[PDB]
Length: 190
Ligand SMILES: O=c1ccn([C@@H]2O[C@H](CO)[C@@H](O)[C@H]2OP(=O)(O)O)c(=O)[nH]1
Image (tube, rainbow, N blue to C red):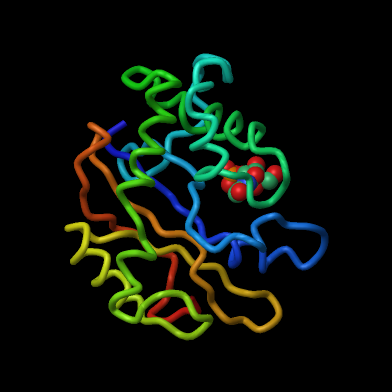
């Protein structure tokens, strides 16, 4: 791998697309971790053969993980962590063992407070239209590099909503670099 995509999701928006059934994310008001995805030549590396998920290796992080990395779609946090490890984490296991991988995601979340970086500039979430350039600009000013913005379009109204924010890191997992791909248009609701 040559870099990482640290992906955070906005729970209310994610769950807004679940028009049927329960969705725990509907009641959260902060960005939470979706995943830490190793990258290679502009694409995500997935399903690499590696070690099976072992909860005992991250037992010391259970408090932080239940708070910062909850499953927002269903009430089963461990299943989500196991899925993320098997699908993404194994691809960077040559340098980051399971414990280090989850610790890395936690440290990244604690050091990349999106709402805190937007609130002062009147760019916090309020269900109104935001500019892609403005949001990327505020985050670049605070963190030093451009983030990636990901959006989803509502099937009924065709309105675009911000659902995830990506912070791009070099292969060392600590050096921030500019992201280069957005799925958001010029404007979206946030
Ligand atoms: O909080 C969350 C956010 C996303 N997911 C993803 O959706 C699929 C549900 O079975 C899960 O497989 C997982 O897929 P991922 O996008 O890699 O594919 C959750 O389960 N919980």
